[PDB]
Amino acid sequence: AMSKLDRIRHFLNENKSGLAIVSDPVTVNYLTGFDCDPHERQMFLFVYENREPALFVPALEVARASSVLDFPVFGYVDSENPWQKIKAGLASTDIPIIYAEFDNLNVTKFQGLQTVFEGRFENLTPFIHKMR
Ligand code: NA
Ligand code: NA
């Protein structure tokens, strides 16, 4: 009955978190069936506890992602600041507890996410391993 995104949302809800930020391309593909290596660019899947998800990708990937996902996809061209684009595109960025994949995120991306999101980050990686 439960989809993989349903399982993420159940986990968030159990742990009083409004949002998971999924960054590992392997996890994005696992959860959604969209397979993308962003290389050095930004990709994040935003799995809200009680809203539809959104995927943020380089602009080049928006058409393909949109063709295989049934929730909103948005992106950025290289002349745009991706942190500003995320902030402008997401309605909700004040979430007290946010889950993210600490084994995947580098400190640079973590610092970027911290410029967008007001809240405390917790580690999603153990749950992702448990799912698989
Ligand atoms: Na779509
Ligand atoms: Na912050």
Image (cartoon, rainbow, N blue to C red):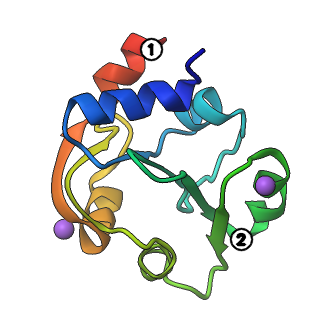
Q: Residue at x 63, y 80 (%)?
A: 78
Q: CA distance from mark 2 to mark 1?
A: 30 Å
Secondary-structure class at tag 1: helix
Ligand 2 in which quarter: bottom left
Count the marks: how many?
A: 2
- The image quarter containing residue 33 is top right
Describe residue 1's horizontal placement relative to residue 16 as left or right. right
Q: Name the mark nearer the viewer: 2 or 1.
A: 1
Q: Residue at x 56, y 62 (%)?
A: 41
Q: Is mark 2 within 8 Å of ligand 1?
A: no
Q: Position of residue 62 (x, y in %)?
A: 75, 63
Q: Which of the numbered marks, if any, corresponds to residue 59?
A: 2
Residue matched to label 1 = 131
Q: Position of residue 132 (x, y in %)?
A: 49, 11
Indicate whether 117 appears above or below 67: below
Q: Residue at x 34, y 38 (%)?
A: 101
Considering only order in the chain, which callout, 1 or 2, is on the residue closer to the N terminus?
2
Q: Residue at x 32, y 68 (%)?
A: 93
- The image quarter containing residue 96 is bottom left
- Look at label 1 and name its amino acid: Met
Q: Identify which residue, 9 or 114, lies in the foreground.
A: 9
Describe residue 51's horizontal placement relative to residue 25 as left or right. left
Indicate whether 34 appears above or below 107: above
Q: Position of residue 40 (x, y in %)?
A: 55, 58
Tell me if mark 1 has few (under 14), some (14-19) or many (20+) residues whose alpha carbon lies within 10 angstroms of its own: few
Q: Which of the numbered marks, if any, corresponds to residue 116?
A: none
- Look at label 2 and name its amino acid: Ala
Secondary-structure class at tag 2: helix
